[PDB]
Length: 267
Image (cartoon, rainbow, N blue to C red; front, side):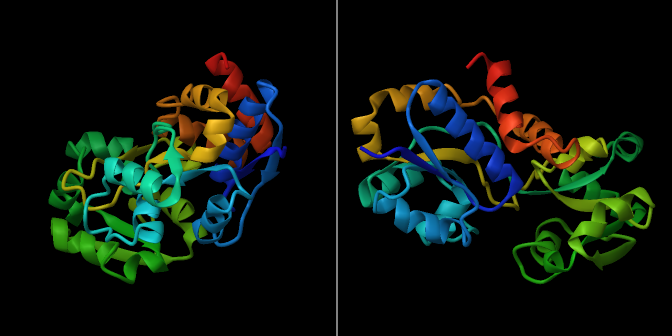
């Protein structure tokens, strides 16, 4: 007899997710131990999960694809393959998908999107001489980001600006830039009321969030599977943006954010 251990990676989004899992199981009288903010993320969570010292966490499909399964991000992330390999090689179950994808995208103002009819990356590339683009230094470094985006879409931005990751949204507000990279769950999408564009050629890989849990734990706690499945498809990108906004902008604790979310779902 030992409480089920919910692990998370160090990010604020991950603390919210860990509290959603923990509070939901606690509501059903299943004892929980929180192991939040594990340095190194998956590479240190995964060995503990296989050894039974963690029981569950929220993983992103593309992260499992590249880090645990050693597959290339230039090949489309395949959920069915992930689920099968996780069961067979690791005795781990993906419960399902929460409903959101946390990956790179590109954003502009809603006014500029309406002015130029911009909905997709290809639209932004078509109109890119009217845009000054900004991103963090790392985004300009390898083929997985800006360099590859240029090979896929033929952008001709009027200017390019690299800066500290924490200055992008501020630089957009000042008009130093008028297009930038975002992550699709960023609180700042809601805060700044940004238009997030569609990656029509599928350049950026998929990082769909889902609960990974030991099959041994589901065998011993069959009700845990039924309970956790109630979260399937309940958190789309806009919902995750809002929960992140509550923590990062409204300064609400991840635990309270998670509690209020579960209550809104009737769980």
